[PDB]
Length: 394
Image (tube, rainbow, N blue to C red; front, side, top):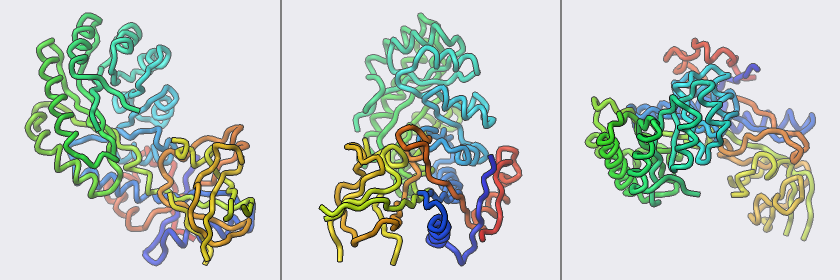
C-alpha cells in the first residue's frame, strides 16, 4: 500500500481538487470518491497539543480505520483506543506497540480478552463485575481503568458500584490503575465535567485505601474538532486537573478523540444514478450500506453551476436507504454530482454484499505549507511515514 499525497500551493484549494476528480471520474467509470485533507488531521493534532499539552490522545480507531489515517496519527505520537480484536490487530500490524493501545469495548468477549493477553495489550476499561471476572480469569497482566458513568447508549458504572468493583478486584487479583469517563460532544452543558472529575478523585481515593496504585485518568472522547469546543472543555477541566490530578502526581491524563481528528478532513462526491418525479426523489451511487451508515443512528451541495423539495436515497432502494428525507434542490439529472462535506467519521466502511463490493476511491491532498511543518517537526523522516509519497499536485 502506497498513499500518494498531492501537495497544494497557495493558488489551489479543495474545490479545485474536487473539480479535477469529478472531471476524471466523468470521463471514466464515474464512481463516488472521497478527498482527504491530511494536513487538516495534522492541524488537529497540533491544536490538541497547544490547548491540552498534558493530555495524551488515544485515537478511536472505529471512527475511521483507513491505514493512512492511523499511520499519520501514529507518526504524530497518538495512542489508539480499540474496541475489537481486529482493531487491535490492525494497529499492531502497522507497528504500534501494545503499550499505546487501550481495549475499550463495553462488552468484552472471552476470546478478545485472551487475544489481548496473547499480544500483550494490557490496558483496558471495565464497568461491571461479570466483565471483571472475565478479565481476571483470562488476562493475568491486565491493567484496568474503572469506567464511571456521567449524567449528560450510555456506559459506565455508579460510584457506589466502584467501591464494590474495587473489592472484587482485590479478591480476583486484578490491577486497577485508573478511571475512565466520557462526556458527549453534543453536551454543551460543560459542568457535567465537574461532577465526573469529582467522582474520579473519589475513586482514586477509595482505591488508594484498598492498596491500588492509580496512575491513569481517561477523560473520554467528547471533542468535536473545533478550537472553540476544545477550549470550552479545557476551561472547565483545567483548574480541576491542576488541583485533583496535578503535574508531579505521576497520574497520566489521556483522552479518546475520534471524530475530532477526521470528521471535517474528508469530503465525499457522489453521482445521481436514478430520478423519480412524485417533488423529486434522487438515487445516488452511495448510501447507508456504504459511506452514510451513520444515518441509521452532511448537507448536500450541487456540484454544477427554481428549488424543489427533494429526497436522496442510496442505490439499494431498500426501506433503510433514504439518506435525506427532504431538502430543497434544483431539478437535477442523472449523472449529476452532489458533494457532502465533513464525511470523515463513521463512513469508511468495507466493500460488502450489501454495496455490491464497491467503495469510493480515496484521494489524498495536503497544502505545501502543512507538509513543510511536518518536515520541520521531523515526522516525514519517521519509518511510520514510509508508505506516503508526497508530490506537487497536477
